[PDB]
Every structure is written in C-alpha cells, then in structure tokens.
Amino acid sequence: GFKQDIATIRGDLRTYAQDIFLAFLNKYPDERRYFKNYVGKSDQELKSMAKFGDHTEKVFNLMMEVADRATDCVPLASDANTLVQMKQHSSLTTGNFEKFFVALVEYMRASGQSFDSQSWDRFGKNLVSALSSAGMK
Ligand code: HEM
Image (cartoon, rainbow, N blue to C red; front, side):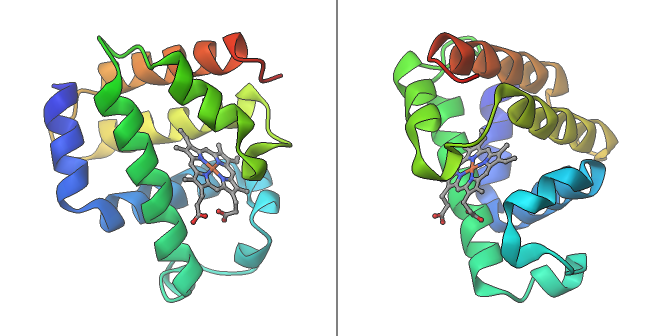
C-alpha cells in the first residue's frame, strides 16, 4: 500500500526521484522552462549535474515527508502551506502539480512493481485541493 510505497521510494530515493522527475519533464516538456539549467540536456546528461541529483532528491525527500505525515492520503494543511509559500514555487499554479502527479502515477502504473497507484493518484488530488485551499492559484 501507500505506506510500503513510501518505504520503497525511500530505499532508493535518488533513483526514483530522477526517474520520476525525468518522466514529468519528458511528458510535459513546457515545464522544463522553470528549470533553466536543465534546458538542452538529455536524461543521461542531467544525471551528471550535481544540482540535478541533489535537487531531485531534496524534492522527493519533502514529498515523502508530506506523504508520511498524511492521514488516509490527505496531507496536512501546514505541509500544503509550506509548498505554496516556498520562494521557488512563487510562479506556480495547481496545474503544475497536477501534471507532476499524472506523470508520477503513470510511472508507477508502468513499473513492474506493485505500487499503490490509486493511492498516489488520490494523494495528488488531495494535495492539489489542499494547495488551492491554501491559496495557490
Ligand atoms: C509535491 C511536489 C513538489 C515538491 C515536494 C517540491 C519540493 C521542492 C523542494 C524541496 C525544492 C528545493 C530543492 C533544492 O533547493 O535543492 C524545490 C525547488 C523547486 N521546485 Fe518544487 N516541489 C514540487 C513540485 C514542483 C513543481 C510541479 C514544479 C514546477 C513545475 C516545481 C518547481 C520548482 C523549482 C523551479 C524549484 C527551484 C529550482 C530547482 O530546484 O531546480 N516544483 N521544490
């Protein structure tokens, strides 16, 4: 289930973080504009820029903390608030996050593994609701 998925992802966090982030960018290429240093780089090229592996790992660490603190895939309003108020997220809207979670859920479905894809889809929906409830446009 969802708790085990947190454990699976944490066990190899940099690998899943890179793969899922790349799946997002490659599914939604317009989103790469927000990540100036990644423009014009292939998957394997990104995998040698220090900021890439370090940024993606930090993003997924936070996402796992938010997931772990959730109750029945509903995140804490304080964790939504943190994500809205981050300087790095100031120009984002909820659609950016919707896209991210579409890519994440698609990744999990395509994986050979028994990820609880439906729980991640619900978590993403509830996080987007919570971002909106916290004032994200
Ligand atoms: C639940 C989803 C997300 C989480 C948990 C998350 C978390 C974070 C964290 C922890 C950082 C700081 C990384 C660092 O300084 O090393 C970060 C930076 C950033 N986030 Fe997010 N974020 C998420 C979704 C998004 C989405 C959907 C976008 C854009 C489409 C985005 C755009 C950025 C940008 C532009 C930065 C700064 C530049 C960079 O880190 O490469 N984030 N985010």
